[PDB]
Image (tube, coloured by chain):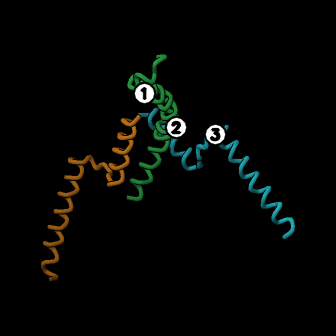
Chain colours: A cyan, B orange, C green
Amino acid sequence: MSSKLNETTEAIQRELEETTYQFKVQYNEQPMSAESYLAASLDDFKHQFH
Amino acid sequence: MSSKLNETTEAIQRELEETTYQFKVQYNEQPMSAESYLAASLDDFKHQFH
Amino acid sequence: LTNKYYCPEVFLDAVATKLAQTAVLFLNVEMLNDFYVRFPREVEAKLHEH
């Protein structure tokens, strides 16, 4: 485990970078949460209803 | 106390009638809470922002 | 324009209009749009916690 530990640490830092890169190119880093989506769709609907 | 108990119980029933009746005519017996007003003016504010 | 160095004012104003126009494109997408999506959310939480 410990021997693999450092090479694993480096690969992990990389896959964290690439995960960031697609989070940048396809989503523009827009953070999302379940309660947020729910709050906004609710409000678009309550606008509609207004 | 036991003697006055009667006229005081009548008069209490009277002042509960009058308040109740005012609650029917001035507020239609409409349920209200602080939160409800706050929610409703909040949504108005949201429509304007929109 | 070939004597730019003799006329600093018209050159610097040229630079200022250009920078202003392409910075307005990035600004509109990034800051403005993010404000339109994140403002309702923060209103609702902040009014709750108050």
- Secondary element at image label 1: helix
Decide: is B18 above or below A18: below
Q: Residue A27 carries which label?
A: 3
Q: How many marks?
A: 3
Query: Distance of mark 3 from mark 1, alpha carbons?
Result: 37 Å
Please identify, in this view, whether the residue under mark 3 or under mark 2 is nearer the observer: 2
- The answer to whether residue B6 is left or right of residue A7 is left
- Which residue of the protein is positioned furthest toward the top in this rendering? C1
Could you tell me residue A41's position as x and y percent?
A: 53, 40
Graded by Cα atoms within 10 Å as few (under 14), some (14 to 19) or many (20 or more), the crowding at tag 2 reads few
Q: Which of marks 1 and 2 is nearer the N terminus?
A: 1
Q: How crowded is mark 3: few (under 14 residues within 10 Å), some or many (20 or more)?
A: few
Residue at the spot 40% in from the left edge and 22% down from the top edge: C7
Report in which chain the residue with disc 3 lies: A
- The residue under the point 48% across, 39% down is C31
**Whether residue C40 is situated above or below residue A47 in the rendered picture:** below
State which quarter of the image contains the N terminus of chain B. Answer: bottom left
Three-letter residue code for mark 2: Glu
Q: Nearer the viewer, mark 1 or mark 2?
A: 1
Q: Which chain carries label 2?
A: C
What residue is rendered at 16% in x and 74% in y? B6
Q: Is mark 2 on a helix, strand or loop?
A: helix
Where's the C terminus of chain B, which quadrant? top left
Q: Mark 1 points at which residue?
A: C12
What residue sits 70% from the left and 42% below the top?
A: A22
For badge 3, the amino acid type reads Tyr
